[PDB]
Length: 242
Ligand SMILES: C[C@]12CCC(=O)C[C@@H]1CC[C@@H]1[C@@H]2CC[C@]2(C)[C@@H](O)CC[C@@H]12
Image (cartoon, rainbow, N blue to C red; front, side, top):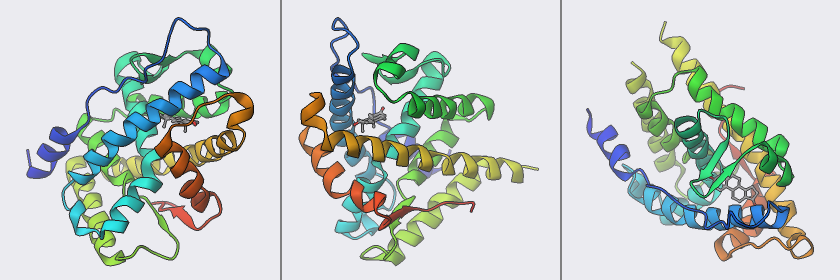
């Protein structure tokens, strides 16, 4: 109904295929290379989504790219959890229409423990009865949920932007106080999942040539330049709850 939800609903990216050959057997190299390629493809959509968000041009240009390059993992995981919930009721991880992870592929990817936590996130959309509007509002907040400890180039504009995206989530929610507690808690729970994936993908990139896993260009750069800033503690998530 407001101008805010109109925009989020209008800019929400469509379907993104991974390009996975489902005829080949489920090897560690094949699954991860297809996930990597899906990441490269989704990263193009996340950029164009982010730039079309209300007030996103208020940020400094370096801060615009920085906030995208830090928050992409959590954003994509959260959207994937939503796809998994809506399509297959959180039974499998719906990374893309041509890349759906069953229990076997959770195991063959050597990421079973991480896939379990992502499936658990997907089940929370069902357990908490999250609406599409709450999903979109929450997802938009995740873009503004990880920053350098030293701060951004223009920190005031980020703070003002983050404040307003919190306000919009509180609005579309509305002893209802428990709701906001729960949604903030669910948003916080994305961050530990994203950190495990940051560690996994970083380790995988280092050893990629040995295990024949293919990393595309933007993924290789971001995982080698931006992700280690997060893993070294220079860049950290903004939690709601301590
Ligand atoms: C973001 C992606 C791809 C987009 C998505 O739907 C969620 C998914 C979560 C796991 C990521 C994957 C991109 C490729 C990664 C980073 C692998 O290198 C290891 C974990 C994978």
